[PDB]
Image: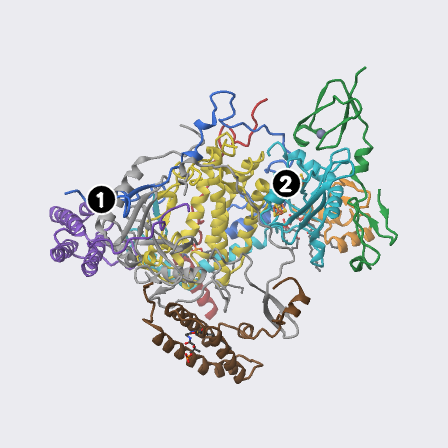
Chain colours: A brown, B purple, C orange, D cyan, E green, G red, H blue, I yellow
Amino acid sequence: TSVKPIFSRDLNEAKRRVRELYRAWYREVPNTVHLMQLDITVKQGRDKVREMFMKNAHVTDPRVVDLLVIKGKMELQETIKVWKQRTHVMRFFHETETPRPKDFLSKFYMGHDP
Amino acid sequence: LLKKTTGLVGLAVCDTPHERLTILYTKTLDILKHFPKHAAYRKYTEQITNEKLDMVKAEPDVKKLEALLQGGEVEEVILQAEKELSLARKMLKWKPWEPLVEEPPANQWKWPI
Amino acid sequence: MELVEVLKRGVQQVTGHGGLRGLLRVFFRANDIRIGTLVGEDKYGNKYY
Amino acid sequence: TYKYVNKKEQESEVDMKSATDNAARILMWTELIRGLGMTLSYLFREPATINYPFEKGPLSPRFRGEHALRRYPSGEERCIACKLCEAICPAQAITIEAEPRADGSRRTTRYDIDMTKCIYCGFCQEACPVDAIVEGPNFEFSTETHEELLYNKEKLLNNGDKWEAEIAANIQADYLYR
Amino acid sequence: GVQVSPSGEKITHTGQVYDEKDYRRVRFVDRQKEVNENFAIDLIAQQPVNEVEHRIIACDGGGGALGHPKVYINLDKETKTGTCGYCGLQFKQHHH
Amino acid sequence: KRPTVRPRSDVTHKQLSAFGEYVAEILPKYVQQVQVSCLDELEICIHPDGVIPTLTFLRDHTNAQFKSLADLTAVDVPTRQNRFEIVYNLLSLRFNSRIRVKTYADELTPIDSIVSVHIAANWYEREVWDMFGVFFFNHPDLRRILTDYGFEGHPFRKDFPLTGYVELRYDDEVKRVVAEPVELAQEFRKFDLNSPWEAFPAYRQPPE
Amino acid sequence: SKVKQDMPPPGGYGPIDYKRNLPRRGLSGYSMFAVGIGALIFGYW
Amino acid sequence: ASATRVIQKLRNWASGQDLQAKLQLRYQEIAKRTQPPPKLPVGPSHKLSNNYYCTRDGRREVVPPSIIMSSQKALVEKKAVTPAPPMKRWELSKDQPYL
Amino acid sequence: EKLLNIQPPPRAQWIRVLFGEITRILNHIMAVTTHALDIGAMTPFFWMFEEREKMFEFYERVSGARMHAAYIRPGGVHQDLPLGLLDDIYEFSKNFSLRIDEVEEMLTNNRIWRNRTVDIGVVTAEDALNYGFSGVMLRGSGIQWDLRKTQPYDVYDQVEFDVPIGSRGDCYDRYLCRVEEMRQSLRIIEQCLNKMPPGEIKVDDA
Ligand code: SF4
Ligand code: SF4
Ligand SMILES: [Zn+2]
């Protein structure tokens, strides 16, 4: 049950790195919306960033948190230097994809998938 | 005479190849004396350096020296000698003569599964 | 000389496609006025030279 | 062994005649003039352009073109639904379904080749034990919709009936090598 | 032989035809459903039965290496011809 | 003698065995296994901590001179604890030889990058990270190199599906190229192409 | 029958040139400089 | 090949090469498109005796690699060696050493 | 084949070496002429692509595909050569060095090409070794290394050829190396045509 750390000895400085990454994303969102001609507002982009962080918010392993921070920094660099395009940025919103309903009756009416 | 070019890009001609090889080999031996006596790297590197120093003291001609050394050009031999010296410094820092750091898992190198 | 021989080959290529109408037909369809040995003709009307 | 492509051996020293030759080479653009002369020679050569579609580039009997399903001289289909072509198809471009026929013969009920998926490699025609599936030499079968390149058994049998006069001759010319 | 549906659509040699209420005939609307006219079952029915003398015959489909793998058909049943499993040719033993 | 069997020379096997003993006794701190294949190829399996010393020694030793890294790759064997086997093929032009150095990793233990030893390891380790998710310490710029921007998952892993999870198409409502969950008009038909009979008795594993 | 195969002729193939072959053409530098200078002098006169 | 002698001399002078000896257009020197049928030879294993497959099974002579040392199996004045003897220097070409 | 511990027959090995050298001529034609096209001259591209069309005819005559032959397989090659193919390969190769001489006349001594290629992208030998370069890059930087000479395969130890070595490590030296090894590939093609042996095509192991 004793493992080798990546960057963080425990969860506290891992959360510090998470807060730093969230700060960088929060600062970079308005520049992205201004630079790439995005239909979205600045509020929607920061909401999406918060949604992604809260999607990953359930993890408690410092190594997994460090790797998530590394991946987030890679995506942040891909957004800072314009390598992600408008399509790549708007892929986070899934606006063309209809969502599967979460209720048993709708899943029963649609098909056999649980 | 003097070699016009070494035939390799970026490898300048050494005017005095014998004394440069001599000082590189002596510095390598001097830093090899700081290794532990049971270090296999120390023993093997001392063997190699002593053989090359013996032939560089024996042969005064550059072409026959290259033929004896069998390391390409004498400038390549000088470059290999200084890389060996830097490796000796790094290996003294690393200390790899110690026992194995950690055993692998039982089926780590078992192929096929 | 050989220039007059080239001109002879040219005038026979011009007057070797039947008439003026045949020359114009082959020149505006195939963009080519070379004379070849008629190897055959298929049932659909294609000529092969 | 090895050789030098740009290393010069010794020196040519300096001479008044050699200096004047190099001066004339620099000033009068001699290598540029001979490059012009090379292009002029190519201008006065004969072009290598064929008159397509009235002239076609040469091919061989081994040429792998549009797929076809052949028959025996009796008219029975050669295919026996063995799915060796489907098994060896590297792109999984062949779909085969089969059942016994009304006379008990082992025949396909579905033979589809996705020509948009096929890589035109001939593995099907070299894995077929009865020479049923072949790549006949047709290559001018480009379509205007994606659907028309999704061949089924009717299309492949029609191709085999259309190109049998040429496919049989190519197999006759080729089969001793394979 | 090629037969037509009550819808008028040609029935393939596999017996496939769309139903009257099947919407997938719209792919043939203003186009054609191409059906191979030469039915191999009828064509192999048209072949005469080969009358041979031996009890066991060998078939390779003709042409040697251009045919099918060479198999052996046992013509012992006098009430039924022996059919080659590859090419569909029928053989019968001549007992006269 | 036999026209269908590869000729075998024992001198290369002897030389590679001697050099494997040489490297193993020079570096006992990191070397875990040394083997020579019947194809006359030398493999040295080391601890992940000794990647930098082992690669540096092989590049800069007078008797090794493996100055050229042929390639760097990973093999996903998802039945061991450390599923990613990192493989370094190296070429010595001085001695006209080739060596293979292996180490191991899992999804959460990064290994040291050898960009300071070979510069080709930059793009090679970028490819390894992009395709397997093996992080590399002290890399100058580690990021994806072959996948699409924003691609989620490492596709050369065994558990990653062949077709992936998303597919792209042009949507005219949004006038963009958009990603959808993958749907195939024809599913990839997997085949069970494994004979139920043992082919090679020399590789018969003992029963459990 | 006899084994028939794609083989070279029994006398071997002919020699195939592969070396770099530049024509080494053109007139001397003295002659062309003399022609140019003479053209200059005639034009000036 | 249908070029007049004037154009041939002009092309040869302009290129500096004798173009007519080596034409880049194929006229008649090529092989005929129809060939006599071949008869390919058989391999060395096409014999009716002394041809057991176990005596020529090269695929089953592969053995697992030999472990020179192991951390678990072995559980562990000589000269230093090299992976191979040093590569001999290439000789300069006697055909055309310089361009 | 190394994993299978089987060897292809000698005729298959000679065919593989011959087509490897034909392919080397194709690839170096593409490299040199498209490099010259990127610099600005396209007439060598057109001439050498007519030559590429003839070599594609050779590919189609042996395999049925002009590019993706799938001809060389583990155990040898897929089929034997059709009759007359060796004669047509000889007829192509006896005229090809003139075409190389044509491109070399067009480009090599041209001062524009020398300005575009000389002292451009200079790579030292140690840097090339550390960056992991191979083939034309190492030999352009001056490293005497070729796998066909050092670790030979098939019958490359039986053929004889020279290895072009640069001395300045630039675009001009790499271009000269590619042209000279095109000439050496032609030399190996001549040797393969003269020394093609009889025998089978695949390994006699079903
Ligand atoms: S040619 Fe190859 S890819 Fe195409 S159908 Fe045949 S086996 Fe499949
Ligand atoms: S390999 Fe031939 S006989 Fe077998 S299913 Fe395919 S086409 Fe039919
Ligand atoms: Zn039959």
Q: Is residue A12 above or below residue I90?
A: below
Q: Can residue H49 be seen here?
A: yes
Q: Is residue I187 above or below residue A7?
A: above
Q: Is mark 2 within 8 Å of ligand 1?
A: yes
Q: Identify the secondary structure beneath mark 2.
A: helix
Image-based side of H52 in relation to F173, left or right:
left
Q: Is residue F108 above or below residue D152?
A: below
Residue H64 x, y percent position in the rendering: 37, 40
Q: Which residue is mark 1?
A: H81
Q: Identify the secondary structure beneath mark 1.
A: loop
Determine whether label 2 and label 1 are within 8 Å by CB: no
Q: Can residue D6 be seen here?
A: no
Residue F199 x, y percent position in the rendering: 47, 36
Amino acid type of the residue tagged 2 in the rendering: Gln
The image quarter containing residue F8 is top left
Residues packed near mark 1 inside 10 Å, few (<14), some (14 to 19) or many (20 plus): some
Q: Which residue is mark 2?
A: D125
Front one among H19 and A48: A48
How far apart are labels 2 and 1 at the CA level? 54 Å
Amino acid type of the residue tagged 1 in the rendering: Val
